[PDB]
Image (spheres, coloured by chain):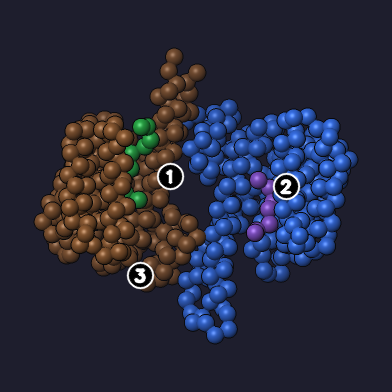
Chain colours: A green, B purple, C blue, D brown
Amino acid sequence: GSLRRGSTC
Amino acid sequence: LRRGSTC
Amino acid sequence: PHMERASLIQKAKLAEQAERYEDMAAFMKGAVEKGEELSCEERNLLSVAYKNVVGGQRAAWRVLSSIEQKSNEEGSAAAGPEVREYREKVETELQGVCDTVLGLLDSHLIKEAGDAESRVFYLKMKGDYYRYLAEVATGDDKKRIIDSARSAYQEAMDISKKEMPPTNPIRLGLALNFSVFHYEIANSPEEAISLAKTTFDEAMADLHTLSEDSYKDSTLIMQLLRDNLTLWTGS
Amino acid sequence: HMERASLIQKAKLAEQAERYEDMAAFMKGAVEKGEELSCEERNLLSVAYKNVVGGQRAAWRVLSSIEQKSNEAAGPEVREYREKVETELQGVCDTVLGLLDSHLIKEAGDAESRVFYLKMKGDYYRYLAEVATGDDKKRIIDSARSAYQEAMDISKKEMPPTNPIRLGLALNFSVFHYEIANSPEEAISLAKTTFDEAMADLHTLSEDSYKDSTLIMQLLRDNLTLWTGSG
């Protein structure tokens, strides 16, 4: 599964 | 609901 | 330090992809200031840049002015010079951008010398940016501004009616904006409804002949005319 | 026009009007008055600078992708303009980090307020590390690790595992391990531990609290799914 990682928000 | 102009 | 014309156009395309429209505007301003004519692609880069810049300023001004109008209502708290001060800050900034665009148009872009499509494009642009000034104008200067927008749009209308077919997207867009000017600025809802109805009907009577590519740009603006007409006439 | 209360008022107005550079400038000026920020005021500062750097990072990624993809027509303008955006991004991080060191990070106050400012210090060094290339890269990466580790120590000592500030800190530090520190094992581990520990406490939660906690927990779960490749 390819998407972008997630930081705060 | 707001009047459309260009774009 | 690559500040030749081709490099400025290149950086404006890069600024667009990066959604940095204030940068894109300044690269396009510098490109215009070289003194050469803009191509159809280059005219669009200039319009997209400044439309995004003023778009944000207008949206902000509307929010602040709406809050300011609530604070001046009968029986409210009605205190706080902050809203007015900050609405004035945004407004001054907005005015600076319009004055920059209008200056480029008068000093470099609008020429008697030019092609029909390009002259209409620039004169429509001159009407739009005077319309944006008129949205925030309240003083004695409001009439001068409203007149300046009418002259630009009327001069553009005359060229489009003489040199362009009723299905032309530049002509359709101009007529849409001028009808918005009539409704919102000139307080002429009858002229607005009429112009929009006429523009849509004349273009509809010619849709049959339109090529595959032209049909998409034209029908897009025609839907904008139809949406405004639905809103203005209530149907 | 200048009084602290007027600056806080104008930053709230700038937020409503989606004018984030102005919001940042008003909040910077409010911080520079020398007083403590409330929980509300802390968030206005965060939102303000997060939006400003958010746009700069997004732009830098687009430009850098065009610059690195062009291999074997390239462009001197791509590099020059990527450098312009990068210098501007760096200026914002340096301004935030300056405010944190000169006015916000203090000897002690409430744990929550202390974690928030060290998480911030961590994040803005992480943003510098995303664009860092020289011999600077190591010291920047180290500075983000110290800031994050110091906030971890406070959160683990003073906060329960379900606390949203603690959860958010651990999520960002795990992103630091993965992306920056090139430690996918530490990242997966921290995210797994953080999620599992908070899952074991989630019952003793209020509706308001629960919503903030489960939001971060899904960000953790999603990172994990992507990092481990489990589905």
Give the residue number, with chain letter if any, for mark 2: C223
Residue drawn at point x = 24 percent, y = 39 percent: D176
Chain label for disc 1: D
Count residues near mark 3 (Cα–Cα under 10 Å), then give few for <14, some for 14-19, many for 20+: some
Residue drawn at point x = 80 percent, y = 58 percent: C192
Chain label for disc 3: D
Instruction: Specify the amino acid type for callout 1.
Output: Gly
Give the residue number, with chain letter if any, for mark 3: D4
Closer to us: mark 3 or mark 2?
2
Q: CA distance from mark 3 to mark 2?
A: 49 Å
Give the residue number, with chain letter if any, for mark 1: D55
On the rendered structure, is C33 left or right of C235?
A: left
Residue drawn at point x = 82 percent, y = 37 percent: C207
Question: Residue C171, image x and y in percent?
Answer: 79, 42
On the rendered structure, is D185 left or right of C72?
A: left
Q: Secondary structure at mark 3?
A: helix
Instruction: Specify the amino acid type for callout 2.
Output: Gln
Q: Quadrant of residue C203?
A: top right
Closer to us: mark 1 or mark 3?
1
